[PDB]
């Protein structure tokens, strides 16, 4: 369209996602599937949302938390996944 309504953070969110994703590849050796699951979630999420402030909010939250709590990374991974489950563009249920 023209504007979502607030500032957009597409590049930031993309990056933040990668920042978190790469991070996951570093701490989720037990769950290398988590990145694909993350990627999937994000990829299948709403591009508007991925470019929206909310994802920035969510992302900035989890990344910052994840670096402090790489044990809670799954919390954050699961969060973002839930987030992406929540704000998917063309979902189904999953």
Image: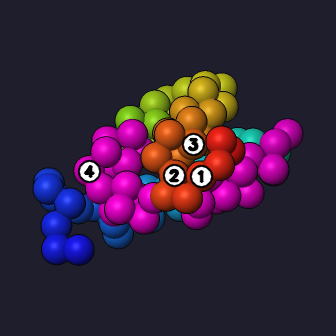
Residue 83 picture location, percent across and down: 50, 39
What is the CA distance from the residue labelled 2 to the residue labelled 3? Answer: 6 Å
Q: Is residue 73 left or right of residue 46?
A: right
**Image marks 1 and 3: residues in contact by CB distance under 8 Å:** yes
Q: Is residue 22 left or right of residue 67?
A: right
What is the CA distance from the residue labelled 1 to the residue labelled 2? Answer: 6 Å
Magenta stretch holds residue 31: yes
Magenta stretch holds residue 5: no
> The magenta stretch spans which residues?
30-59
What is the CA distance from the residue labelled 4 to the residue labelled 3? Answer: 17 Å
Q: Could you say which disc has been placed on residue 79 in the image?
A: none
The N terminus: image quadrant: bottom left
Of residue 3 and residue 50, the one placed in the foreground of this image is: 3
What is the CA distance from the residue labelled 4 to the residue labelled 1? Answer: 20 Å
Q: Along the polypeptide, which appears first: circle 1 or circle 3?
A: 3
Above-or-below relation of 32 to 62: below
Magenta stretch, main secondary structure class: helix
Q: Along the polypeptide, which appears first: circle 4 or circle 2?
A: 4
Report the residue marked by disc 1: 91
Report the residue marked by disc 4: 53
What is the CA distance from the residue labelled 1 to the residue labelled 3? Answer: 8 Å
Instruction: Estimate how packed mark 4 is, as few (under 14), some (14 to 19) or many (20 or more) residues with alpha carbons within 10 Å.
Output: many
What is the CA distance from the residue labelled 4 to the residue labelled 2? Answer: 15 Å
Q: Is residue 48 left or right of residue 73?
A: left
**Image marks 1 and 2: residues in contact by CB distance under 8 Å:** yes
Q: Could you say which disc has been placed on residue 85 in the image?
A: 3
**Image marks 4 and 3: residues in contact by CB distance under 8 Å:** no
The C terminus: image quadrant: top right
**Image marks 4 and 2: residues in contact by CB distance under 8 Å:** no
Residue 68 picture location, percent across and down: 49, 29
Q: Could you say which disc has been placed on residue 88 in the image?
A: 2
């Amino acid at each position: 369209g023209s504007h979502m309504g607030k500032k957009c953070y597409k590049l930031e969110n993309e990056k933040l996602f990668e920042e978190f994703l790469e991070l996951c590849k570093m701490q989720t050796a037990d769950h290398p599937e988590v990145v694909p699951f993350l990627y999937n979630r994000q990829q299948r999420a709403h591009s508007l949302f991925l470019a929206s402030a909310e994802f920035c909010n969510i992302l900035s939250r989890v990344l910052s938390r994840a670096r402090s709590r790489p044990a809670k990374l799954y919390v954050y991974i699961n969060e973002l996944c839930t987030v992406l489950k929540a704000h998917s563009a063309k979902k189904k249920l999953n």
